[PDB]
Amino acid sequence: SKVTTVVATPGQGPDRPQEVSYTDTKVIGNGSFGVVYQAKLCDSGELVAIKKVLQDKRFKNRELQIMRKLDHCNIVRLRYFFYSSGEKKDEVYLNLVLDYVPETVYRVARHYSRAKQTLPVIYVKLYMYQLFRSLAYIHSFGICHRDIKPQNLLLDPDTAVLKLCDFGSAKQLVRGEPNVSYICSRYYRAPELIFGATDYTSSIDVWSAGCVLAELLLGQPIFPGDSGVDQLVEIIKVLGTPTREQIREMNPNYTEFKFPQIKAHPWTKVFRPRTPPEAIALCSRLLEYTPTARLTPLEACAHSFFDELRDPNVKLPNGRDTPALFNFTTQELSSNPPLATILIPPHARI
Ligand SMILES: COCCN1CCC(CNC(=O)c2n[nH]c3ccc(-c4cncc(OC(C)C)c4)cc23)CC1
């Protein structure tokens, strides 16, 4: 195909643009944001994703500012960004050139569902552990992703590396500064949001992660609501009716749903009989009504459900070694540095 040459600015480091050539553009996604393409870097031959968004010339793109400060093995990397012009007065596009990753958790999970099989729990551990690490990192800056779902969990199936993508809903949450409640993808939406809360925290992402974990264990979404309000009905069918205290802790803006009383369905009867007890226990501490009762991402990483990953003999099913799971920086551990003793086993220590 015809080569495109641009002058692009590196994601990290000082603003020093470089000539970049790419080719073989292919549309691979769209949304309210604009369009995402696959492309191939001419010089190195590496595939990349290019996220193209209409951007107002006189304002700053929030996703860009967030992407320029993130540097983590479980977060898709911003290689470069550049501006391109459309065929209209002041029609400017921001182009984000990101790492290409060949699969998603959604796609992998679906393969197992269609074959009427469960994803082996080793992959559930690996994928969930890496999601929680990515969340521990972004939360340490005060950034809440606000769109955790299987479709935004990229994976390389050969190395089992997971990378979080799509920071178009991400935001630095500030105590006392309101936020919109109609956020996140419905099935993964925290109950406080359904109650119209505008004063919420990063614990909304932990709820969404819990929904991902349950989905990988069940073979299908645990809370498949057909509307914003029916989402709460689905949650209630498992968790039971929230108490008045639990409702208060969710900081709701309305609660006039007039829900009939429903008993909680026991967590052990939700999943198949052979589900590991530690998976169930972890899940019960993520999917909690009271936001502050939920595990932090770092505490989730230290859960006994991930003990297999801390074993020195662990290997991937393809024979290869596990990716780097314990190379925690001081930033990643800042919420609770004493957890390093559990998070970093003897053989991984330096
Ligand atoms: C020949 O056919 C192959 C099809 N194949 C199917 C899986 C696919 C997985 N990879 C990615 O999505 C992928 N990689 N790097 C990214 C970097 C950014 C994004 C991304 C960021 N913000 C919003 C997005 O919105 C979509 C959710 C609509 C996507 C995705 C990505 C590879 C293409």
Image (cartoon, rainbow, N blue to C red):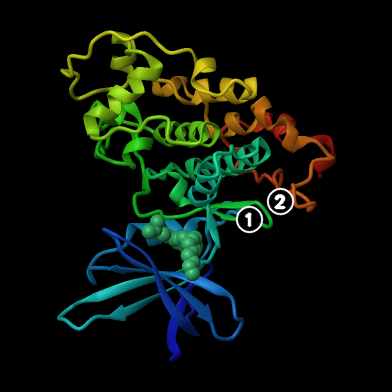
Q: Residue at x 61, y 24 (%)?
A: 275
Q: Name the residue under label 1.
A: 157
In which of the image's four quarters is ligand 1 placed? bottom left
- Residue 312 located left or right of residue 181: right
**Amino acid at pointer 1:** Pro
Mark 1 and mark 2 residues within 8 Å of each other at the beta carbon:
no
* Relative vertical location of residue 297 with respect to residue 272 in this rendering, above or below: below
Kindly give the residue lying farthest to the bottom in the view shown. 2
Q: Position of residue 289 (x, y in %)?
A: 38, 20
Q: Residue at x 50, y 36 (%)?
A: 219
Q: Quadrant of residue 306?
A: top right
Q: Which of marks 1 and 2 is nearer the N terminus?
A: 1
Q: Residue 235 vs residue 138: left or right? A: left
Which image quadrant for residue 311?
top right
Residue 123 on image: x %, y %: 64, 42
- 197, above or below 147, in the image: above
Identify the residue under disc 2: 323
Q: What residue type is labelled 2?
A: Pro
Q: Looking at the rendering, in which quadrant would you find the N terminus? A: bottom left
- Residue sitting at the far front: 115
Give the image location of residue 246, x and y in percent. 34, 14
Badge 1: how crowded within 10 Å, few (<14), some, or many (20+)? some
The residue under the point 55% across, 73% down is 47
Q: What element carries label 2?
A: loop
